[PDB]
Amino acid sequence: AVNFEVKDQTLMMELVPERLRGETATFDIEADGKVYVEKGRRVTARHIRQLEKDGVNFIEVPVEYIVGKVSAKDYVNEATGELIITANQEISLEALANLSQA
Amino acid sequence: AVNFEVKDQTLMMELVPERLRGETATFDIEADGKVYVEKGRRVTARHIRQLEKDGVNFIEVPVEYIVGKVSAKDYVNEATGELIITANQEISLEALANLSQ
Amino acid sequence: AVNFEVKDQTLMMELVPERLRGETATFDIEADGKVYVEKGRRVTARHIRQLEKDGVNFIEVPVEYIVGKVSAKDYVNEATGELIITANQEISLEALANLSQA
Amino acid sequence: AVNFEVKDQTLMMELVPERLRGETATFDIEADGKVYVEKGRRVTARHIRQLEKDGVNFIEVPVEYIVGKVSAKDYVNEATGELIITANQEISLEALANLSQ
View (tube, each protein chain N blue to C red):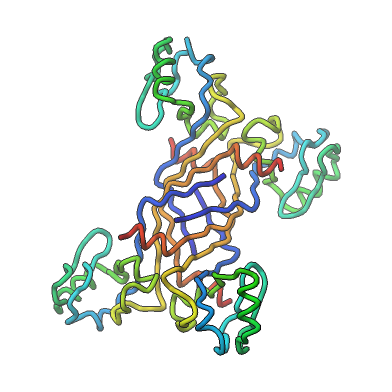
């Protein structure tokens, strides 16, 4: 009766800025379409303050993080997590009425 | 990646109590698990009073209503309709990770 | 714990082609991004066969149809209906864990 | 326009029965409404047998597991995880019509 097709997916976790400084980024440090540190760059003090200036409290993390395929990072808070799924939800009213009738 | 297993379904619509009184119900007149008048029975002034006392301004309407299998009624306002789907949304994190890669 | 933001919505209903011929379209007759008859045009035999050639068994109808704000049309099957909602579903894992903990 | 009222939630993960035997459970070992071993109890060879006989290859894991409040265990495979959200999806047809206009 209801099909749910995933078009995109993103995981976000709370930044711990005090642990990010000096890391070499293994994935782009980004939020809301803006990349603050490119993969392979070492995070500078300015990068930290640029995130802060923009009010970036959550950053993107690879979705694979949630199935254990990314070694855990001290610069995100493990007690947090926001999963955003963009989907096309197809609801058959006919099929629902048939569930209801039965 | 995401399955949506439907366990129950209903519409809800705003009630126009003036137009209900005197009619014979074609579906249970119901809200929040309480049935006020059963299908096949006449709606009394007492029923109308009970609905008002309980503050019932929306009632359940079968999803069949939306595909014409239950015919239209004056005492529910189609402009106000809601579809409530009770479901288990089964999200495969493995599948989402696969999609991300 | 879960927010569901609607980005787009479409209603589709099964076409009854035998009742569409000769109608003056009051909304574009379309499916899958292709407009077959523009609003205000009278539907010709060719339009019917063009829909058929493309296998168009369902057409778009204004969503308002489902709240009774479009007078019913004999050229769609009233016993049908497919509602497609494009949404951003935001799932707070933290909030869900808190529901679970409680 | 759409509210998603959560009524229950769990993860599920693939079980590695060899790594469970002998451990003391920190959450009920459970599938499809049957609890095999309660939180705080040791998993026996008999428990392992029961799981196998019932064909239980995925078990429930608390959502707390995903935010670190329940610590990681060798006997569930995080690569396989699912999140199952039981909810009432309340779709306002009035609101969808409003959005369409």
